[PDB]
Image (cartoon, rainbow, N blue to C red):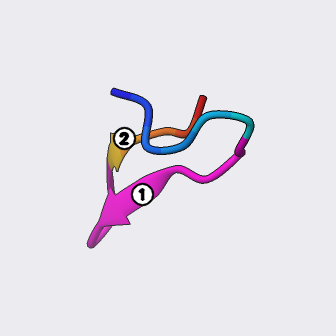
């Protein structure tokens, strides 16, 4: 699950990575 192409943004919920950026 990528949340952003050309981006280095992973999303965390509390402390759980819910996605990363592509």
Count of all numbered marks drawn on residues in the image: 2
Q: Which residue is mark 2?
A: 19
Q: Distance from label 2 to label 1 (Cα)?
A: 5 Å
What's drawn in magenta, residue-wise? 7-17
Identify which residue, 21 or 12, lies in the foreground: 21
* On-image quarter of the N terminus: top left
Q: Which residue is mark 1?
A: 11
Circle 1: element type: strand
The label number, if any, that marks residue 21 in the structure image: none
- Return the residue found at the far front: 5
Q: Is the residue marked by circle 2 packed among few (<14), some (14-19), or many (20+) residues within 10 Å?
A: some
- Looking at the picture, does residue 22 appear above or below residue 13? above
Q: Which circle's residue, 2 or 1, is located before the other in the chain?
A: 1
Residue 20 among those drawn in magenta: no
x, y percentage for residue 12?
Answer: 37, 60
- Looking at the picture, does residue 12 appear above or below residue 14? above
Query: In the visual, does 21 lie left or right of 2?
Result: right
For the point 74% across and 36% down, the residue is 6
- Return the residue found at the far bottom: 14
x, y percentage for residue 16?
Answer: 29, 53
Q: Are marks 2 and 1 in contact (CB under 8 Å)?
A: yes
For the point 54% across and 43% down, the residue is 4
For the point 27% across and 72% down, the residue is 14
Q: Is the residue marked by circle 1 packed among few (<14), some (14-19), or many (20+) residues within 10 Å?
A: some
For the point 60% across and 28% down, the residue is 22
Query: In the visual, does 18 lie left or right of 12?
Result: left
Circle 2: element type: strand
């Amino acid at each position: 699950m990528c949340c952003g192409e050309g981006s280095s943004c992973p999303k965390y919920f509390r402390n759980s990575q819910i996605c990363h950026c592509c």
